[PDB]
Image (cartoon, coloured by chain):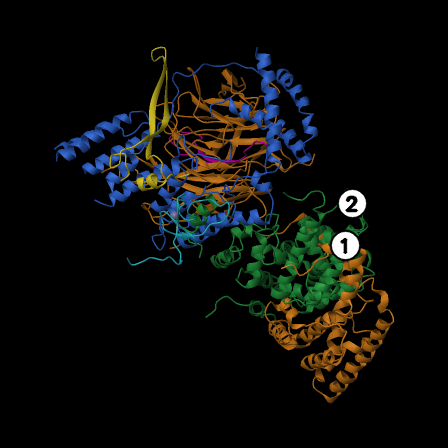
Chain colours: A green, B orange, C blue, D yellow, E cyan
């Protein structure tokens, strides 16, 4: 029945097909540019041509879903679109961008560096990351006041001097203390954390008192339904490590409610004699002035909830703010606790050393 | 249902829940993916004298730090539950459980204290007067065989160690030290786990010996032994603690909650019934608290874990004529980053207890009510990040804090005047000469895109996306809508073909998560948000909408005419069946 | 933190149970020696027993006598020393985590991760939260949300129907809009009563031996739909299509149908009738403490 | 799978017999009830008279 | 739609090598529905 030994072709044809399917959904539903496509045909063209310039029945192929996302990101980043990995994670974990099947029923940083050596970033594309929108994304993601965008943008310039890249790739696998935390975004997040920590816990002109660290913390902590927070809950549900699942334990009836809403909407994007017996069996018990508020609405009101702006246990407030931020980042950027702190650790010693 | 319509669809009661009320009380390879078998703290009223006197609520606690210590002190109850002043004593090894028992009102309501440990097993007496407590260590016995005892039950010291058990007796007060006879053993080579357990059932010489596989009733002082009715199949004995003056029993096995109790006098089981509560967690223990009233006698069932600080509760009641029923599950949390080693107890419900948590030398009284009519972060992984400072590294941190503080001053005073000039004729001069200034350079790079077009080995030309080397170029305007109009008329200008094209709005979508048509409404939204806060909003929000609009400025490769060229020139060098693998517009 | 209602897993856990029961067998083999494969696990787990209406237990009286020490240190390590090595061979083929797993379960440690805890993943962690919210909302009497939960749950292509009491109480306090209660109950019964291993039973099961949940639950609850009266001859006609007919408790359900029909020589035959099924339910089971209560009632009838 | 009743109209049209199942509770005894075994069997589907107590009609 | 469930009367069509039974009920006996077709009769 099924092909043998050179279904390499059908493999690459369901793969290619599934990719173009995803692009259809990101220009259409995510209002990308038509140019993305040609950028993608070029990159997947490059690596298709490289596996077909190492093609052999002695076959060594590893086209994963991760490869699909990797060339979307790769291509986006040449195009300097302000999209970041966390966009992609949210997208795929939400069953919105098709993924999590072979043809539905009818490691990202590491595979982007991997592809990023597979065909070379340097003399074919421009692999500067869209840094400044990552900053904006980040300050808005906290409720940090717009000064911190320049705060961090400065520390960024201080260590890197504005330059950011996509290969820490030589084919090698045995990596230890050499060339890792060389994927840029992670360093940006690290800088971001550091900034908040130094910046706050060391402005002796403390313009920022003993307490607005607290009010900041609480306006950060208040579980309140918008699209975004609801999303981050939806991500939290598929994030590998506790605690971020104790989190669904602590949801509010409103959070749970918008949850079941999203449930019955995007699990009509569900997957999969007795078959019709369960088509009926399930169709026995029933499948089935605007309220909750927008992003900048919520954002406004926490900015106001702190608008009363105008003592080493504030170090505490610093720490719990940092660790909350951290958590949001871990789920949002699909990495590990221990990964993050490896990076911020390394790069903080990397800042002390290039100032000391 | 069963009795109500034997007698010839909803619950008896309405929907009850669970509230808190808290107080402070005490305060004392590489493989922790497993755990040993240990428990480790008691609180119980015991009768010191008994020259017509009452009981005194005592705590027996553990000072640990360095493993090996034992604490005793009285607790004056009323409501805020306290102490007076401490009294302590260690042993050369590690405490594995402290227990102190009380057989019920058949008798003389009294006790004294006992504890078992890594290579030693001891039992203590006590007298007390004037709020000092004086206890008195009736001799240990270092481990006769080089084994180790799981459980003590208790005037009968009964030990259980990794299978084999012994009944034994304690001395009366002095030097003489504790002997035994009547031994025995359960044993099951295929019980890999080390915990077994012994506890009284009924009262006269009927014990229960347990391992995570089976339940063994052993009637000593006769000769008797039974494997009860399950074992070793779909679930594990997970815990068992004896409820009730003498004749009550509570067993946790996976999800079944089991109440055994007596019948035919001695020696019985109950398949009365059970609830089922839901894991695979090897760590799971139970404890009961009991309360009374006329029409029932209710048991509150606390099953808790070592993995999460949720507490899982069920409720049974004892009707005079050996009768039990249930109602519906309820579960609570409390503060995070840890988990419990002690949960232990003593038209509404009051249930109250104390907990200890993993690796927190801290005892907390808790109290739970039916209704309402009436992070200390030391994540060693993160603080080690946020300090990592000598003294010259404290001031080394303070350095660039000051540096970009005065720098941010430079930014503020700089931009201010540009903000002054918002709509001047001057700023029109600048947006003009700047706009087609740019245009001249943009043409130049388009020319050295003529000269090197024939490459067709890539499609990303040189390095493009810039202000295109004017640094004076960017920074100096202030109006956002006249700068958006600049760009709209520059895109309009190079509308002569073979050019990069990109549409910002559809992309600000990614930013504010709503349709962001104009470049301007983008600035509006941000300015609302940040005018609420620390405002130099007007300025910064302009300065960052300027940075974003720069960072994104679609200055980039020649288009379509040039993708469809390398697309095919590599699409060729790939042979054959891969020339048809390179397939687009599927369906 | 609650049992999951989907088939546990694929993964490692099989090779772990391999190591476990293989080693078990080597130690117990050498142990009977000194006292003188899915299938290896299968034989291994195999040769082993597999004032109110209490299904009373089997108590201690004709059972056994006492043993006295079998197992010193020097003598246990005898039985331990060899099979641990044979284990050293296929331990060489299982994975590092399961090397250490077997190592520790063999030292007598006990793991403190669960099969759920270690089975990582977007989708299952989501199901875990979905089902938690189910069990929580049902504890809370929040039948509406609860219901939404249950529906999105069973919608998911992973959940087996091991969460039926889920509806059987859920849809039961939800008079509101949906066919319910008995609907579900007798549905469950009709579907899972024929042919038409682990990961199983007491509250789910198939034919040939008994089936707690659906069977007895609809089988009384319909008699409660007749306490709705003050129907019966229907419940007792299709109750009166046995056999499993060792379902003694259903014999008592039958006798109950007759005491409820009894509430002229017709009523006689109904009381004669209950008198018959009570003792044909002395089959065994074990109910009704004194049947002389049932029979004092039957004499209040005999008036 | 949960069975359905069979109405003779079906048996007619399918041109098969209309039969109920036949069941036997069988006592397998050894040594004069020293050991005995109850096992129910099925001797095959038994044709049933229409409009009788075993006819669904 | 050539066919009818011999029981629930549900109209249906079939295909080559298809389970013969009501997609709804599952009754494995099926009827062939009569369709518009020209048949002659004399009124004599
Ligand atoms: Zn049909």
| Residue A201 vertical placement versus A170 (above, below) | below
Q: Which residues are magenta?
A: B36-58
Crowding at dot 1, Cα within 10 Å, few <14 / some 14-19 / many 20+, comes out as some
* Residue linked to disc 1: A47
Which quadrant does the C terminus of chain B fall into? bottom right
**Label 2: which secondary element:** loop
Which quadrant does the N terminus of chain B fall into? top left
Q: Nearer the viewer, residue A253 or A43?
A: A43
Q: Nearer the viewer, residue A15 or C251?
A: A15
Q: Nearer the viewer, residue B307 or B23?
A: B307
Q: Is residue C280 magenta?
A: no
Estimate the x, y position of residue A189 in percent, counting from the top left. 70, 58
Q: Describe residue B171's horizontal placement relative to residue B514 as left or right.
A: left
Q: Is residue B52 magenta?
A: yes
Measure the C-alpha gap from mark 2 to mark 1. 15 Å
**Label 1: which secondary element:** helix
Q: Nearer the viewer, residue B116 or B146?
A: B146
Q: Describe residue A30's horizontal placement relative to residue A61 as left or right.
A: left
Closer to the chain start, of discs 2 and 1, is: 1
Q: Is mark 1 within 8 Å of ligand 1?
A: no
Q: Is residue B137 visible?
A: no
Q: Is residue B464 visible?
A: yes
* Residue linked to disc 2: A56
Q: Describe residue A216's horizontal placement relative to residue B107 as left or right.
A: right
Pointer 2 chain: A
Q: Residue at x 54, y 64 (%)?
A: A226
Pointer 1 chain: A
């Amino acid at each position: 029945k099924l092909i043998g030994h050179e279904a390499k072709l059908l493999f690459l044809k369901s793969f290619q097909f599934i990719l173009k399917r995803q692009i259809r959904w990101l220009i259409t539903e995510m209002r990308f540019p038509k140019e993305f496509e040609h950028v993608a045909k070029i990159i997947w063209l490059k690596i298709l041509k490289t596996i077909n310039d190492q093609p052999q029945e002695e076959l060594k192929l590893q086209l994963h879903m991760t490869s699909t996302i990797s060339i979307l990101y790769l291509a986006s980043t040449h195009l300097s679109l302000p999209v970041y990995t966390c966009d992609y994670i949210k997208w795929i974990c939400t069953a919105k961008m098709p993924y999590f099947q072979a043809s539905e029923i009818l490691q990202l940083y590491n595979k982007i560096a991997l592809t990023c050596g597979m065909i070379h970033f340097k003399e074919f594309f421009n692999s500067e990351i869209s840094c400044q929108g990552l900053l904006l994304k980040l300050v808005m993601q906290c409720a940090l006041p717009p000064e911190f965008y320049f705060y961090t943008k400065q520390v960024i310039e201080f260590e890197e001097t504005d330059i950011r890249n996509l290969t820490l790739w030589e084919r090698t696998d045995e990596r230890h203390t050499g060339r890792v935390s060389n994927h840029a975004e992670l360093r940006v997040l690290s800088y971001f954390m550091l900034t908040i920590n130094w910046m706050l816990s060391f402005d002796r002109d403390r313009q920022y008192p003993l307490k607005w660290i607290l009010s900041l913390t609480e306006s950060l902590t208040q579980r309140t339904t918008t699209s975004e927070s609801i999303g981050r809950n939806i991500v939290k549900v598929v994030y590998p490590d506790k605690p971020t699942s104790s989190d669904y334990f602590q949801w509010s009836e409103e959070e749970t409610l918008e949850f079941l809403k999203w449930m019955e909407k995007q699990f009509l994007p569900t997957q999969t004699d007795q078959k019709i017996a369960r088509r009926k069996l399930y169709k026995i018990f029933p499948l089935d002035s605007t309220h909750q508020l927008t992003f900048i609405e919520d954002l406004q009101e926490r900015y106001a909830k702190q608008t009363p702006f105008f003592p080493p246990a504030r170090k505490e407030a610093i720490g719990r703010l940092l660790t909350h931020i951290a958590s949001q980042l871990l789920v949002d950027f699909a990495i590990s606790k221990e990964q993050l702190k490896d990076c911020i650790s390394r790069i903080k010693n990397a800042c002390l050393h290039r100032m000391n | 249902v069963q009795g109500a319509s034997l007698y010839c669809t909803l619950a008896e009661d309405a929907l009850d829940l669970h509230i808190v009320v808290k107080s402070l009380l005490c305060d004392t390879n590489r493989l922790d993916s497993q755990y040993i078998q240990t428990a480790s703290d008691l609180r119980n009223y015991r009768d010191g004298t008994e020259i017509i006197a009452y009981a005194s609520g005592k705590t027996g606690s553990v000072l640990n730090i360095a493993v090996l210590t034992r604490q005793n002190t009285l607790h004056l109850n009323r409501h805020n539950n306290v102490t007076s002043i401490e009294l302590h004593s260690p042993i050369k090894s590690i405490k594995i459980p402290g227990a102190s028992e009380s057989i019920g009102r058949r008798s003389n309501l009294v006790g004294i204290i006992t504890e078992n440990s890594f290579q030693i097993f001891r039992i203590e007496s006590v007298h007390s007067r004037s709020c000092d407590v004086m206890v008195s260590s009736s001799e240990p016995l270092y481990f006769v065989e080089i084994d180790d005892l799981q459980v003590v039950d208790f005037q009968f010291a009964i030990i259980d160690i990794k299978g084999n058990w012994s009944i034994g007796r304690i001395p009366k007060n002095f030097n003489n030290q504790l002997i035994d006879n009547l031994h025995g053993t359960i044993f099951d080579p295929e019980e890999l786990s080390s915990w077994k357990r012994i506890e009284w059932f009924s009262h006269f010489q009927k014990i229960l010996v347990f391992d995570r596989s089976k339940m063994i009733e052993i009637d000593f002082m006769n000769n008797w032994q039974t494997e009860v009715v399950q074992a070793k199949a779909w679930s594990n004995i997970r815990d068992y603690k004896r409820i009730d003056d003498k004749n009550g029993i509570l067993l946790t096995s996976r999800e079944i909650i089991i109440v055994g109790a007596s019948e035919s006098n001695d020696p019985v089981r109950r398949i009365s019934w059970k609830h089922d509560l839901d894991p695979d967690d090897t760590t799971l223990r139970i404890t009961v608290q009991k309360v009374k009233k006329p029409d029932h006698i209710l048991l509150v069932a606390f099953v808790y874990s070592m993995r999460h600080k949720r507490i899982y509760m069920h409720v049974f009641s004892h009707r005079k004529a050996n009768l039990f029923q249930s109602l519906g599950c309820s579960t609570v949390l409390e503060i995070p980053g840890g988990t419990p080693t002690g949960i232990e107890t003593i038209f509404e419900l009051v249930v109250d207890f104390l907990v200890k948590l993993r690796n927190s030398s801290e005892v907390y009284y808790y109290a739970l009510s039916n209704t309402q009519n009436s992070i200390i972060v030391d994540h060693p992984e993160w603080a080690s990040l946020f300090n990592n400072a000598d003294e010259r590294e404290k001031e080394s941190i303070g350095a660039l804090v000051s540096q970009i503080k005065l720098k941010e001053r430079e930014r503020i005073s700089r931009v201010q005047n540009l903000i002054e000039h918002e709509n001047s004729h001057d700023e029109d001069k600048y947006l003009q000469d700047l706009g087609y200034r740019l245009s001249i350079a943009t043409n130049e790079l388009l020319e050295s895109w003529q000269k090197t077009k024939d490459e067709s080995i890539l499609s990303g030309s040189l390095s493009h996306s810039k202000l295109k080397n004017l640094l004076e170029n960017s920074d100096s305007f202030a109006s956002i809508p006249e700068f958006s109009s600049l760009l709209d008329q520059f895109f309009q200008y190079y509308q002569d073909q073979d050019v990069t094209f990109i549409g910002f709005e559809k992309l600000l979508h990614l930013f504010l998560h709503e349709d962001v048509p104009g470049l301007d409404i983008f600035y509006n939204k941000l300015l609302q948000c940040w005018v609420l806060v620390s405002p130099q909003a007007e300025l910064l929000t302009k300065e960052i909408v300027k940075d974003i609009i720069w960072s994104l400025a679609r200055l980039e490769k020649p288009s379509l005419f040039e993708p469809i060229q390398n697309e095919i020139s590599r699409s060729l060098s790939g042979p054959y069946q891969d020339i048809i693998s390179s397939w687009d517009m599927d369906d | 933190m609650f049992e999951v209602p989907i088939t546990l897993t694929n993964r490692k856990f099989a090779q772990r149970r391999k190591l476990k029961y293989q080693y078990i067998n080597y130690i117990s083999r050498r142990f009977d020696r000194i006292s003188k494969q899915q299938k290896k696990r299968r034989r291994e787990r195999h040769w082993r027993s597999v004032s109110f209406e209490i299904w009373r237990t089997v108590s201690s009286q004709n059972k056994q006598p006492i043993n006295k020490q079998k197992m010193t240190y020097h003598n246990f390590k005898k039985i331990e020393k060899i099979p641990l090595r044979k284990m050293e061979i296929p331990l060489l083929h299982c994975t590092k985590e399961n090397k250490l797993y077997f190592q520790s379960i063999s030292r007598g440690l006990e793991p403190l991760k669960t099969s759920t805890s270690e089975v990582r993943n977007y989708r299952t962690r989501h199901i875990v939260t979905l089902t938690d919210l189910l069990h929580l909302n049902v504890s809370r009497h929040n039948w509406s949300l609860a219901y939404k939960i249950f529906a999105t749950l069973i919608r998911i292509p992973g959940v087996q129907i091991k969460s039926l009491w889920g509806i059987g109480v859920e849809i039961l306090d939800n008079l509101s809009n949906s066919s319910s209660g008995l609907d579900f109950l007798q549905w469950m019964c009709q579907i899972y009563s024929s042919k038409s291993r682990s990961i199983v039973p007491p509250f789910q099961t198939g034919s040939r031996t008994h089936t707690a949940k659906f069977a007895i639950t609809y089988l009384w609850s319909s008699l409660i739909n007749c306490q709705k009266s003050m129907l019966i001859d229907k419940i007792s006609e299709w109750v009166l299509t046995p056999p499993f007919m060792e379902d003694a408790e259903v014999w008592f359900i039958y006798a109950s149908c007759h005491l409820l029909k009894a509430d002229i020589n017709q009523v006689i035959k109904h009381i004669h009738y209950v008198r018959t099924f009570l003792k044909i339910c002395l089959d065994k089971g074990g109910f009704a403490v004194p049947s002389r209560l049932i029979e004092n009632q039957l004499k209040s009838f005999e008036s | 799978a949960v069975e359905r009743k069979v109405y003779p109209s079906e048996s007619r049209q399918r041109l098969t017999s209309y039969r109920g199942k036949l069941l036997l509770k069988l006592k397998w005894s050894v040594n004069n009830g020293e050991e005995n075994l109850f096992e129910v069997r099925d001797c095959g589907g038994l044709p049933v008279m229409l409009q009788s107590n075993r006819c669904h009609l | 739609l050539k066919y009818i469930c011999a029981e629930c009367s549900s109209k249906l069509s079939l295909s080559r090598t298809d389970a013969v039974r009501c997609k709804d009920c599952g009754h494995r006996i099926l009827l062939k529905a009569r369709t518009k077709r020209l048949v002659q009769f004399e009124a004599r």
